[PDB]
Image 1 (cartoon, one colour):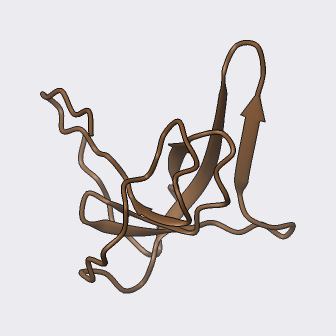
Image 2 (cartoon, rainbow, N blue to C red; image 1 turned 90 degrees about the vertical axis):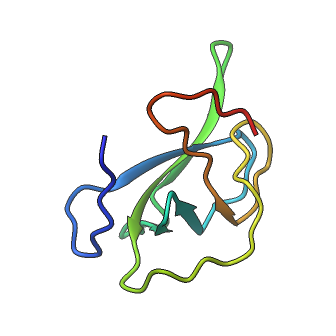
Length: 98
């Protein structure tokens, strides 16, 4: 599917990280630069673990300003990951293990 990079959007982007990650503030998603949504209680962000699996998850929106491609690591989908990272985005038709 296409990926919107609209700052004024209603439709946020969900992002899985590894359980135990710190709250990740910003990611670069296939060109677009996303910042974590915030609630009237905090960051829209959730880590969960049980017998069946574990993960961390946040909702992200794109920031007004883009095109800046900084030097961060890969977001880790099963480890700690780090606070600002680049998300792995496999394009429709490909393997894509880091």
